[PDB]
Length: 345
Ligand SMILES: *[C@@H]1O[C@H](CO)[C@@H](O)[C@H](O)[C@H]1NC(C)=O
Ligand SMILES: [Cl-]
Image (cartoon, rainbow, N blue to C red; front, side, top):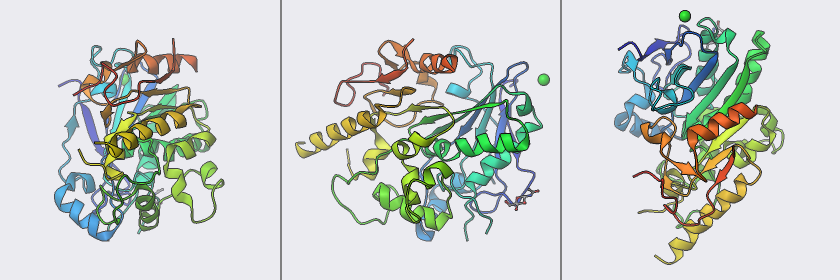
């Protein structure tokens, strides 16, 4: 097929996936478009040697490029089909697979390797030779751990480009399902399994184990040793220099899982309070889209055009935002999961 994204493994083979195989990116160039969409894949993380070994058996794709296919079809925001992607089908499309298990924060060279931030850096620089140097807009986008990666890296990439001599390129971000709360769990549990570890504790261990770096402007706000705060969207958002659009299910499953909810009286309240706290953190975020659904991820799913908030679709909210650089602070007020009719299933 004419329209598939093609795999490029990183020429510098010292920047690697967890297991030492080369990292990489898929690319579909678009004749004539000055819009670049760079997508960071998600899929959790591992914060100790034992959890990582276990992920290596269960989910090897997420720790190695050995079996990556040479092509991939872009879906959602990365689709070249006008019906699937009405404003940006004609964009330069890039998919960066997530094989560092580090929320894209790993920045050192030397057991498992965690080099997420360096993979992004490396992909940006290779792309300059394939046409990124003439871009008007570089949209750094991501889902789940990729979404959080956007927040950790978008200003780093803005700096990388001005340092390399390409200041005219407008760097922006789009974080989907990467906006989490460092809250108290519903029912307590000791941190042992990835999926049920409290978010706060998970990042504390992750950041040390990974040698993870956080954006500089957020790092300065918190004490030495408390860099884990910068993994949380409401804490990193305020000092961002690059513009960022935030897409977040008010009742995100990954959030519920880490809050040790499993799917009552007390639970209803906790859940409904979650939704409320979420809304509160989006109050000063005009570029947001936050439907009251219980779900996780949206932007590279084929059905992303379906969801609406206040009569506006996600592709339309994004296009208006792009144009402002038609409403934009699109947060559902209805208070219980699925109260929005447009939710998916
Ligand atoms: C290649 O990547 C390695 C590991 O990050 C880095 O140390 C080395 O300097 C890179 N090569 C360059 C920038 O030429
Ligand atoms: Cl061309």
